[PDB]
Image (cartoon, coloured by chain):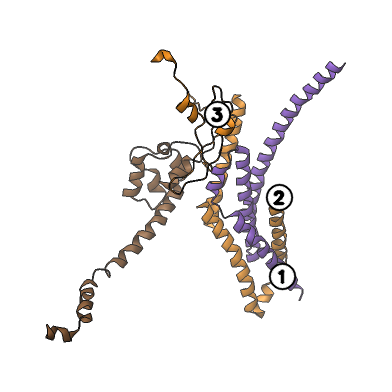
Amino acid sequence: YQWRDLIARRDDESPRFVMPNQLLAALVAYTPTDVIGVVSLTNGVTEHVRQNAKLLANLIRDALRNIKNTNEEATPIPSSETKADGILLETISVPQIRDV
Amino acid sequence: EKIKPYVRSFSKALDELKPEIEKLTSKSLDEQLLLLSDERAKLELINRYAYVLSSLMFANMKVLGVKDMSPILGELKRVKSYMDKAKQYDNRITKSNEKSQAEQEKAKNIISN
Amino acid sequence: NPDVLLSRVINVVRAASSLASQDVDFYKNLDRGFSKDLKSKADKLADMANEIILSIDWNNFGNIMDNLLEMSDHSLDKLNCAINSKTKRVEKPQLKFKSPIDNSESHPFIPLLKEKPNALKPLSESLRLVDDDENNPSHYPHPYEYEIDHQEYSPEIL
């Protein structure tokens, strides 16, 4: 989206002329890692993304690395909650409990 | 002790060039190209970018001492090629402008007489 | 500027060239350390090339040069096409115009108005800069705002 806006404001063209939303969807769904998968998608390919297809292939590779980093982190986060509940019991005095 | 001044000179130049590359490279080229409306200005910035990279690659290869230099040199002529093409176009435009002006002077002279 | 910087680049190049003139294989036997001072200098040079590649975003350099010289070729073809014009061929109006198109939007739209007929307020007073509100960002004030608010409608439409 940012790139296409960048080119559209460069060559003074419409964002859909640089790249239609349907073709962009093919880049998000299929994710071509090479310059071969970028050029040949759906029905046809416009002129703007054809010349910068190498960049798009590079961009997909650039895009891919970030997604991988997030996944490993997530499992750790869930476990702590029972422990968080533990701290309150610790904080409360054992002594009072016999009193009440 | 003969080699040391050469190394020192090179090292100093790199420090000298380093800030300039940082100052030149601060803005993404697409950003710079969007900024200037003129086609003629645009062609200039691009040729410049091609010139610096080719030259820096050239200097790099020399530092390495790699055996064959035909390829790097090939890129530099290509740059010299396009830069010339830029310059040649400007000269033709200037000549046309001069000719139109020349007539005005003749017209002024006739009126005076 | 460009020239000065270009001259500086040229000065770097001559120094780079002189080193090549010297031959050091003889030296390889003598010292490990000499290479490190040089290798670091070489790595600094490579760093700049990498930065250039990032901006564009040996093999990387080659692909980028092809991209740069593709862009350059198009510009001159466009210039020549325009001057020679001065199967169906597409016609585009925008390129022709004397003030070329500016999509940068660096500054808030500046009215193109240079005269103001039927004015109640001076064009002067009309073209002015107002400091931004914390609540609202500053914008140029429509030049006939006053006229629209305070000019009287012809009796006839009413």
Placement of C55 over or under A8, stated as above or below: below
Whether residue B95 is visible here, answered yes or no, is yes
Q: CA distance from mark 1 to mark 2?
A: 25 Å
Residue marked by disc 3: C121
**Residue A44 at x, y percent in the picture:** 37, 37
Chain of the residue displaying label 3:
C
Let me know if marks 3 and 1 both belong to one chain.
no
What's the colour of chain B in the image? purple
Chain of the residue displaying label 1:
B
Q: Quarter of the image holding residue A48? A: top left
Q: Residue furthest right?
A: B113
In the picture, measured across the screen, residue B30 lies left or right of residue B55, that is: left
Residue type indicated by callout 3: Lys
Q: Residues within 10 Å of mark 3 (few under 14, many from 20)?
A: some
Q: Which chain is orange in the rendering?
A: C
Whether residue C99 is visible here, answered yes or no, is no
Q: Secondary structure at mark 1?
A: helix
Residue marked by disc 2: C3
Residue type indicated by callout 2: Asp
**Residue B8: mark in rendering:** 1
Proximity of marks 3 and 1: CB atoms separated by less than 8 Å: no
In the foreground, C119 or B84: C119
**Residue C109 at x, y percent in the picture:** 51, 37
Residue type indicated by callout 1: Arg
Placement of A69 over or under C100, stated as above or below: below
**Residue B69 at x, y percent in the picture:** 64, 58
Q: Secondary structure at mark 2?
A: helix
Q: Which chain is brown in the rendering?
A: A
Proximity of marks 1 and 2: CB atoms separated by less than 8 Å: no
Pair 2/3: label in front: 3
